[PDB]
Image (spheres, rainbow, N blue to C red):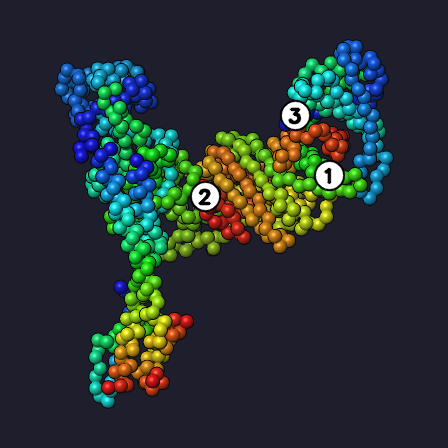
Amino acid sequence: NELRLEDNYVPTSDTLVVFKQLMKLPVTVLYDLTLSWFAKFGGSFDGDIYLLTETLDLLIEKGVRRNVIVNRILYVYWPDGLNVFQLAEIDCHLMISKPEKFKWLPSKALRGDGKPYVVKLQPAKFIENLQTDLAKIYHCHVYMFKHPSLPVLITRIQLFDSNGKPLISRRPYYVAFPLNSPIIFHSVDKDIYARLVLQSISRTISERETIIFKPVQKIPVKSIHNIMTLLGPSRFAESMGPWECYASANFERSPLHDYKKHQGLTGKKVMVREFDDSFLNDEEPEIRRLRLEKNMIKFKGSANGVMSRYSSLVPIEKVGFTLKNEINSRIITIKLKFNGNDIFGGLHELCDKNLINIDKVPGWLAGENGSFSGTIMNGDFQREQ
Amino acid sequence: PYTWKFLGISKQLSLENGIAKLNQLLNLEVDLDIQTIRVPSDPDGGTAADEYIRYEMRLDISNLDEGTYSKFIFLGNSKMEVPMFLCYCGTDNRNEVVLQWLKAEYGVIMWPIKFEQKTMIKLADASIVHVTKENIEQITWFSSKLYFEPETQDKNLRQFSIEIPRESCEGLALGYGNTMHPYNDAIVPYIYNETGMAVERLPLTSVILAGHTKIMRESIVTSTRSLRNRVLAVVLQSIQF
Amino acid sequence: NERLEAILSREQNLLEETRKLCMNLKTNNKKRLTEKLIQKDLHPVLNKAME
Amino acid sequence: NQQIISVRNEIQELKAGKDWHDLQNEQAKLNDKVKLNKRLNDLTSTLLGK
Amino acid sequence: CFLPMSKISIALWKGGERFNQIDLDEICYGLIKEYGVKTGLKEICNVCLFPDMYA
């Protein structure tokens, strides 16, 4: 059952798609990349490692464009094609550089009666166990790397199908494992291959007891950094929006700190709000700056703000809110649908333009439960699946 | 789906002046309709201010050709500033030939019709209300939804919608009580009552009823056979100063 | 096709064994629930517990 | 392929189902309850009778 | 742990005769587990001290 692919294998790939893909990379990452590539697989160049150094050094010393070096890589050093390990390294640097282009989707791990289970994934064991299970079904080549700035482990999985005399590659599948969290991030794809990969991952983790994977949400998240704050292990996972200051915990100092600069002793100046409805009937620049600051606190949680200034901590693309209430001994419901880039950020400026009243802003509309489309019932928010 | 193009009149004109001389330029027969009815602004009583005169005719011979069908519906007053307006549907040469003929006849000049939030919502009130042959007013309800398109930088919030099931519409008007303007006292305040957004201040794109009408500021779209009378009257007051 | 055919036959055999064990466990649980504690030998201090 | 997938899906579903684990749970409670009654009845006969 | 820890156990005698300390441990472990500490200790006296109330 040697269906796994070694590092020396050269899968078939179109030279045109890889031609434009390498153009997106800067010269500095295309320089050192080929140097490690020659140190592992060699090349068709008539020289050793040292000769390939000054020849490539001359190109970067001349400030030459990105096009010619890509042509040299594709048609001179490796004219036949690119290896499977070689292809995986390219996507590794693209993930680190620009993470906005790649989708993500959460998944919760449950076992037994439903208690959440924290994953204790190990790199060495997971590589062979996943390969062994998928060897009998398809050709599998798994390569995982640790995120440089985050504790999340990113796993790259590809499936190969036979045909062009040899086989060809398919679309990749990405699975992200947080360091310590019961939630698994994975790329969204509705394919028969995608279902097999996710199911096989559940089995190899369930060596102790049976574990099921359930999709928490339907709408994907644009960035890995954004999805790490909302659902990964962090202090901002639950408290957000108006409660963002609690996660930062900057307002309260240590009990052993000096008492001279205490908030209670110093005090603060705030605007007296009027509970009488004068918004429908509709200046001091000292009162105007308070009006802008009142909207500043409600949508971000702090007067200074935590990261122009209208952007939120994490953008949300789609939210669906259903509000239910009982009037005249019967249920009255209304459905609100939103769409945009930063829905909660966009709602902030509408208060700045005095289009909507800031006092009568519900907590869910303010920005609480970011990216959680749910139904509000009797003043409480319930997750909708 | 029939799209209606709206249009106003500068000063009151007479249209039945020369139906014989409106045809030879067009080379086919056009009929005439003379009609006036009561439009009760208040159910208790009505003054002489609702005295309305309406004209209607068409330009066609072929009933099979439903696509090439157009109607010119006139209605208006004679005592306020703007006497009347007009509306038409469909695209054809017949939608303008008469229009030039009274371009150079009476000296009235036209202008596109402008709608904003103060008017757009109240049109659905006249659309949903019904009148029977016994002068009894009952309301046929529809699940209205609203379209909002706020202008913003970064396109952070470019379009959002509010949908109301109209059984919940039923539960709102009954709570307020018997009202002749359901969207004054059951619907529009309730959106501000719960979510705190002012519908009128926000830029509104469309108000959609459940399979009856299609209201947008640029043009009104309705799947009915012909437009009603309360709709035209409320349009007239709205465009009045 | 031949190798995967054996895999299909092997997995469904384990599938039947596990399901028939669960069905047997359900029948055994009903057997243990009745005739073992509701009869006359019940303990009055456990009668409140059974209430 | 889906024949393998569909079968494998319900292999995990039956083992990870709440009902199957409930059968395991009810086994422990039923075995414990009969044990307590047997011992508690045994001592009462010993304490009072010969 | 570091918080204070409390232990509960019982022992009974019949005119100076010591009972088996083994079987008396389960009957006190499960009786107060199924009814709580507050109520569980009440029927310990009801069973040990009032055996004729059962017969």
Amino acid type, label 1: His
Amino acid type, label 3: Thr
**Among all residues in the image, which is located at the extreme right?**
B48
Of marks 2 and 1, the one in the foreground: 1
Q: Residue at x 58, y 36 (%)?
A: A353
Viewer-nearest residue: C45 or A285: C45
Q: Earlier in the sequence, mark 3 or mark 1?
A: 3
Q: Toward which corner of the image does residue A213 lie, by quadrant?
A: top left
- Left or right relative to A2: residue B110: right
Pointer 3 residue:
B3
Instruction: Please state, as top left, top right, bottom left or bottom right, where the N terminus of chain B lies in the image.
Output: top right
Distance CA(mark 3)–CA(mark 1): 22 Å
Pointer 1 residue:
B130
Viewer-nearest residue: A187 or B56: B56
Residue A216 x/y as whole percent: 40, 44
Mark 3 belongs to which subunit? B
Residue B129 x/y as whole percent: 72, 39
Residue A340 x/y as whole percent: 49, 34
The mark found on residue A372 in the picture is 2
Distance CA(mark 2)–CA(mark 1): 42 Å
Amino acid type, label 2: Phe
Badge 3 marks a residue whose secondary structure is strand
